[PDB]
Amino acid sequence: RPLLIFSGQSNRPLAQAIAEALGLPLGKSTTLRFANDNLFVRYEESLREGDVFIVQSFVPPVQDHLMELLMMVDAAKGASAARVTAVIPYFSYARSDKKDAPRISITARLIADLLQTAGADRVLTMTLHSPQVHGFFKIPVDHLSAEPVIANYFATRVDLENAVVVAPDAGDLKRASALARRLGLPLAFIDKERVSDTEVRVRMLVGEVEGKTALIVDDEISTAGSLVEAVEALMQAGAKEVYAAATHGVYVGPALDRIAKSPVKEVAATDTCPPKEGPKLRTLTVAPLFAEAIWRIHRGESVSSLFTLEHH
Amino acid sequence: RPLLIFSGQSNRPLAQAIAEALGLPLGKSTTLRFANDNLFVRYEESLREGDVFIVQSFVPPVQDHLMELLMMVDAAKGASAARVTAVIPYFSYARSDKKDAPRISITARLIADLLQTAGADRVLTMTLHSPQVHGFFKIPVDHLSAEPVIANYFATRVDLENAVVVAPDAGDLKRASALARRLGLPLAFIDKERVSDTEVRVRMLVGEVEGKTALIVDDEISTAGSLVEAVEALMQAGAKEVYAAATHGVYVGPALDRIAKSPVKEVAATDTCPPKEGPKLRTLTVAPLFAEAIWRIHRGESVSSLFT
Amino acid sequence: RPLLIFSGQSNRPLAQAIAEALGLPLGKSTTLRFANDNLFVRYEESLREGDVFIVQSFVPPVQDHLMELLMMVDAAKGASAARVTAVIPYFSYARSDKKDAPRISITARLIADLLQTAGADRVLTMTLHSPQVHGFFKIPVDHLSAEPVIANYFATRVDLENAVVVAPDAGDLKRASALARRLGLPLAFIDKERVSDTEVRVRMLVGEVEGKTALIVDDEISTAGSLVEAVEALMQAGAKEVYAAATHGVYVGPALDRIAKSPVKEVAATDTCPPKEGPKLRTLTVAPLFAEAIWRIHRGESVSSLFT
Amino acid sequence: RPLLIFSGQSNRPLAQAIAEALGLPLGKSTTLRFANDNLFVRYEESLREGDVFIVQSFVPPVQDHLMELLMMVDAAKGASAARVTAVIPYFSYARSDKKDAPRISITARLIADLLQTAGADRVLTMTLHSPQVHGFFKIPVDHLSAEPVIANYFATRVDLENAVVVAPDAGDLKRASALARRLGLPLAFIDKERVSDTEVRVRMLVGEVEGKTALIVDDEISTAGSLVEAVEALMQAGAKEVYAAATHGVYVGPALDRIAKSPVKEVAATDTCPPKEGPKLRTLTVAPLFAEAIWRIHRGESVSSLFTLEHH
Amino acid sequence: RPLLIFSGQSNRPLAQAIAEALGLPLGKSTTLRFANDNLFVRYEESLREGDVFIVQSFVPPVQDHLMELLMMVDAAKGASAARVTAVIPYFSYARSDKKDAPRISITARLIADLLQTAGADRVLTMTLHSPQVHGFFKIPVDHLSAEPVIANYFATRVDLENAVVVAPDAGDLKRASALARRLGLPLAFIDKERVSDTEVRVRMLVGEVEGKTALIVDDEISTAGSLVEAVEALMQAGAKEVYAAATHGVYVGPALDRIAKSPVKEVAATDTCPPKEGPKLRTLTVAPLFAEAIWRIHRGESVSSLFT
Amino acid sequence: RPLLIFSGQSNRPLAQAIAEALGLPLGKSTTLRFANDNLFVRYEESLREGDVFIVQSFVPPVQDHLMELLMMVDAAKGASAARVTAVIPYFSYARSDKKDAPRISITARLIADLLQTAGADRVLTMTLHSPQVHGFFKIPVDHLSAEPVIANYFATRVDLENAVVVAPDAGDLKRASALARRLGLPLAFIDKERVSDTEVRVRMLVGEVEGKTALIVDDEISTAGSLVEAVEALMQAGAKEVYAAATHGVYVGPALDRIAKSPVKEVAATDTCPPKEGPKLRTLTVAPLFAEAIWRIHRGESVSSLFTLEHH
Ligand SMILES: Nc1ncnc2c1ncn2[C@@H]1O[C@H](COP(=O)(O)OP(=O)(O)O)[C@@H](O)[C@H]1O
Ligand SMILES: Nc1ncnc2c1ncn2[C@@H]1O[C@H](COP(=O)(O)OP(=O)(O)O)[C@@H](O)[C@H]1O
Ligand SMILES: Nc1ncnc2c1ncn2[C@@H]1O[C@H](COP(=O)(O)OP(=O)(O)O)[C@@H](O)[C@H]1O
Ligand SMILES: Nc1ncnc2c1ncn2[C@@H]1O[C@H](COP(=O)(O)OP(=O)(O)O)[C@H](O)[C@H]1O
Ligand SMILES: Nc1ncnc2c1ncn2[C@@H]1O[C@H](COP(=O)(O)OP(=O)(O)O)[C@H](O)[C@H]1O
Ligand SMILES: Nc1ncnc2c1ncn2[C@@H]1O[C@H](COP(=O)(O)OP(=O)(O)O)[C@H](O)[C@H]1O
């Protein structure tokens, strides 16, 4: 069973870097859009009895990328692949994980079912918005952590002697605590409120940030709305400075303008989504980690062992 | 089980015309795009134990409309609809009906499976690109015919005395021969072959078109490449004039410019796709026909005594 | 389709209270254990073309109750029920909602699939451990909220003037903030982390509790380890007093001894699980609320105008 | 995973020729019919973890052959085969591919679903009546073409200097055009009408047939009704002579009598269906092509490469 | 949902007798064979939102009848039936119920799955070869008993005073003992073993048959090999006379000649299979019993207060 | 694909003996019960792309053992096992194989469906209560026979010169006849009735038992109700003595007391269920036969060949 890697249109540079890290070419496939906006996929060479891995992130245009992935998985099974894995570095619809209003779609579950119907045997992903999304799949899911790559970034960039990890929202405490333990840093919480959409009010601080290098971490940065509020709150609480990181650098709508305007020193994210150009933006490549996971899925070696427990 | 009608963003005017024909309101549902281009759907009122009909055509943006339909079907079942029908007036991906090259998707079949997985109990549709696409569905499909509205259009709009109906494709003749039979006309057909998405090559023309008014009938008009080449080939062959009709007026890319430029006298299509205004374009509404079919599906009355 | 209600052995008192609220008898069904500890279920009368509701909570013995529910669902479909709803007032395995260690079962999802395979057409439940568990089901779930009965309990039973609602867990805030909002109170939360099945470590306390009457609201109380540690941590932080409420009063192992010993003034829970008598324990019945939801599911009326 | 080949009762000679071309014995299986007309299948030896290929064509008695195939696929999965392929050289029910009347079965789709339920992992077939029938299967389908074998036959039999390929029906133009391009021949069309079921009227001819060796090709010959009409029309249009070929030589009811009575010089068909004895009947064996396809399915080599683009 | 009854080609007389007992017409459907022995089915009128019952027994030609049933079920669902019941008065392949040799089909289970895939929502059947075959179906099965019509036949047709009921097979005793109990008679049984499709070897005879009138009751009579060997073995053992009854009078190959030749006095069977005339053969119609069961399934009334 | 064997809590000694007979360690897995009586399973090491076999018998507590098995099968698929086999040495619910009352569960079929839903690819079992239970599974089932091990036991224990096999119930004749043919013994039948639950009446005897060593065999001994009645009937018919054997020594409720009180010389059963201590109880280990079957399933060798036709 040859190992074969293909890409949709979402993140061909990540797919290419993954193939190169495996010492393999990126498989040849074409995606066309007809004048009627219908899609067409075709594998240019045989992938018969292949262990096929198809890379696609849920970035704009999202529904074209979802359909391209469904059609490439379908076409791979139809062309007699032995096994088909959906490599989905950023699964945006993991945010659609609950029925928080009546009569909506739990779209993360619907998409799991659609991927299974299309013929996916497995999923490989990173930093799901919520860990319960794993249970929306019947097929095996290998869920990679960005914890080691994000902690490495900070360890190489900031003054650890004078640093603190800050959660700006109750939901951020678990991921922030993991980072704090990895860097040997104190953990603080900043309870803030957007009052007049130009001012944010510091209600409560637990821990110390005054004159400290504050670190914030999230699963994703979309519009940078939460990043901006936390940084403003932290400078109002007298932080020296703020470094931010996330797994998914989605960077849509006002994100780039907001980051340029914010006093935030730097914003780092992986390449699960194609990076955008910006003076304070940094990229943390996960091509080598996805390549190692794919190698281990293919050979039946331990993907769980890739979650290291190193302390800086 | 109350009759409930809802619309996606593809063709709200047709859905509204269907609701009005049934004497019902169009049900309230929200579709929005988050900043990250992710879709969100919500039914504003209960549809619990409803006989739910969701109207969506496959028109640009097609993948957004496909996903909005899948999400509306899913959310209707999740909101305890008694039955959910995907009313798909135009199913574009019916053209993806065969494996004409290795290692492609038969995307019509894939989408049938996605619609079933999303929770569709049935489909209502009109003029599938090929009749075999009916077999891509496990759930029941009511497959409506445009033949009555197209027959009526030619019967009253064109001189019939020296007319021939032309099938623009040799593989798909049943439609042209049934229309030819219905208007008491002879039949010609074009043997083409597609060169690109936008260009076709006429390899042969069978039948008598010399000095005749030629009536092209097709399933759809997309780029209008097949239409204007068939008109070029009929005029070159000595046709007096050409008229055309299709169910699906998709009219993308160079279509409206190509039709306006072509010597074709008039082009009729239904409103399965939102009509685009043009001097030589005519709309044949199928709202009443979709309404009558929905009423009949709802009540358990014969749909065949209309359709196909 | 007649409305039919049945009970497993887990919570016959709640099922009986639901039946009485609907003005119906509790349907007759036998469950027995053979000498070899194999289960046997039998419906004593026809439920053919019935709208069948089977009440079972996940309380000890939990695997016997799970299997009795699966077997009652299966036998109801095999006896030609028109529709079968698994009414699961307490779904314990909602706590098994994530893969927080390698090579485990996401048991909430497994059980959703087993319930579907057994033949369940729907689920009715209350206060799932996490809202994402709704997405583990393909069949529709009506997910009832305890917020009205818990709000009413605190509003009338405790002094509100100097009160704060405390979320005993930082990841699950929507419940505490909606209760805080509803009572016009401020909000504190505990950032914990579980050390064992019976012990939790409070890593941080956010909000103002000094000299306040603290209202703990949680989904469930199992061993009461999280409850008494949160009370220890609030009193240590200078709270005047603590009251607590949860939907699911599971009260296993050292719970009743731990609550009686704790300075907590009172602990309210619903009857999703059969109440256990204790001087500081109060029962908030949800029988009327399950009855109203079943009537509405049966008739196709809005459940959301109660729930969630 | 050993390669194992078995046969139902429909076309044991083709199954035997396929096995022999692979250098393999035909696997031992018995099919009994009890006095009550119920069927019984049994594999005489282990096929555990085998790559098992079961040959059955849809020839009379068709429903016994369909049920035998379903039961052999079922029994193979039940006996712990690794993989089961339905080798269906002639899939008669591909003609039942549309709802052309209300309240009928689209029997080609129903049979696809029944084969999948029985436990088929894959299908290997040749010349489906319509190409849309491929999309009635969820399991992979390898669809072989008879184009190269039929074009070879004509290239070895007829005067190519004076030959023309004729389509006698609009539906026949695509297959006829492919043959014409392969043999470097002109393509003609003959519009004819059966008027008084003893006479057929030539309405229109496009291209030339007068004094030419006319070639006609179809997917199948059942009753030879369409073959007879085309040949009569072509001799009325002054053709020298007519050679006919098809993939599936089904040859039911009056076919043999009609062919003997027709001026048609010769009628060639493959052995997807067991050939019938007749003076003007010729057989074009596809045992070697099915054997090559099976070899390539088994080894994960390119079945698509078997579709050659050779011109005579 | 209107009650609609249809027949395959296997047993149109029984279907007609069922329709007449319900006061309904037998619905119109065409089955034809194409020249190439491919089947074709068509419903002549709408059965949309129908409660559809399709009658087919597994009698020669059995594979044609199986396929005609699968195709009628499929086409009924494709024509938007509300519910489709496969009424299978005789399910021959219930005899293929075990893996008694390696690498065979358990064909009863395969056919249950094919019937489900074709779209059957339920089965109505009578006297399955083994009761376990009920477990081969996921969809509900109403399994009718012949015991009332067989009991009544022996009670009025034979002298009971010196009678014994004989089970012709030691593994299948529940039928003979329930009939023995119902007629107030003692019970004997034959321990056989099948040598071929047409021959059985009696290895042991248990019970008192000397000078008695022996009543053989079996599920079916196929070749009559087991019947005439059991009669040979009872007369050899000193029985005065033998009578026999079975549900399914299949009567293939040498059966009618073997019965006529055997000293057996009379052989009764139902019309699950079209009766074959013979001097010693009697028909016990089960049309009224199938009609009553269909009416009850249709209306949601108790079938068990008849069946099994 | 490594061969990997794990155990639930039901019969760890049998699982351990099977692993040892394969020359393999018993895989490490933990099962916890939380205070709320909920179960938790975890595989301590990778079983990725493993051929995994999970041993569990349906012994008390039965529903905890059923759920543990479902959860271990689920978790194995979730941890990316290549193949998962449910090794179920005693399938108690095979007794729940018919609808003998209205509105009950055919629980053997329900459990088959639950095992398939959990992700079982295959079942390996021994002495099903009824052979029709095989057809309740869609997944392959290897059904082992205890016939050779039970016949060996008697051949090593009893005076074959003066022995007879007795069926005490019509349903017992087939299994008793097989034993009789294997030991070259006559077969007798004893028709008895429990009249006053302290007395049993011999209605009929066919064959001879007077002064003979009577052998009785069953699929299982639960409460020993049927064993006791047969032995009492046989001593009333003047048997010298009675030896009993079964596959499944379930031994619940009064079984041990009843066997001690009965004149039965000895009662032998396999270790499909953990043996209970008793003076007249003997164990016939099937660990070596299950190990051989697992070896052959894993390697694709003939499991059917393990059914020997030896005569003593
Ligand atoms: N959904 C689609 N939209 C537009 N073009 C398509 C679509 N699916 C396939 N096609 C293109 O159209 C070609 C088929 O054109 P044609 O020869 O008319 O066959 P068909 O009978 O399916 O229309 C395909 O080979 C492909 O290039
Ligand atoms: N069904 C269950 N019953 C009790 N404890 C469980 C159950 N499932 C998992 N657990 C345990 O509880 C832990 C989760 O506790 P917690 O941190 O509160 O997460 P959650 O949000 O799921 O409660 C798991 O890691 C496991 O040790
Ligand atoms: N559908 C069937 N029709 C006729 N005979 C069958 C059928 N299926 C299996 N058999 C044959 O009958 C034998 C079973 O006969 P028997 O010992 O009576 O067992 P059963 O209890 O299934 O009748 C099988 O071994 C096979 O030879
Ligand atoms: N796929 C999605 N992309 C973007 N926003 C989404 C998506 N799904 C839901 N949302 C919106 O984002 C919010 C979700 O936040 P909530 O579930 O309360 O906490 P969290 O931010 O942790 O997910 C709004 O409730 C919801 O409408
Ligand atoms: N499996 C079959 N075998 C034989 N004839 C069939 C079969 N299925 C359908 N037919 C008949 O053959 C005809 C099909 O022709 P039609 O679909 O119009 O064009 P084509 O001949 O290209 O299939 C009749 O419509 C149909 O009744
Ligand atoms: N899983 C089970 N464990 C124990 N007893 C059971 C089980 N399932 C059914 N029973 C009981 O055991 C009896 C079954 O006997 P029956 O089916 O008549 O013959 P057999 O004893 O051969 O199975 C009672 O009918 C039934 O209630």
Image (spheres, coloured by chain):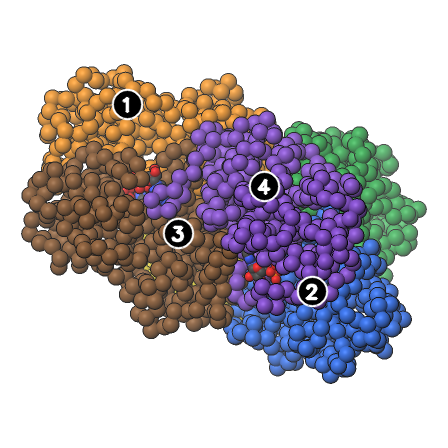
Chain colours: A orange, B yellow, C brown, D green, E blue, F purple
Task: Give how far apart the Cα atoms at labels 4 and 2 are.
Answer: 33 Å
Q: Amino acid at mark 2?
A: Val
Q: CA distance from mark 2 to mark 3?
A: 44 Å
Examine the rendered structure and indicate whether residue E107 appears above or below residue D84: below
**Can you tell which mark lies on residue F271?**
4
Amino acid type of disc 1?
Answer: Arg
Q: Residues within 10 Å of mark 4 (few under 14, many from 20)?
A: many
Viewport quadrant of the C terminus of chain F: top right
Secondary element type, mark 4: loop
Crowdedness of circle 2 by 10 Å Cα count: few (<14), some, many (20+)? some
Q: Chain of mark 2?
A: F
Proximity of marks 4 and 2: CB atoms separated by less than 8 Å: no
Above or below, B143 against F183 in this view is below
Foreground: disc 3 or disc 1: 3
Disc 2 designates what residue? F202
Quadrant of the image containing the N terminus of chain F = top right
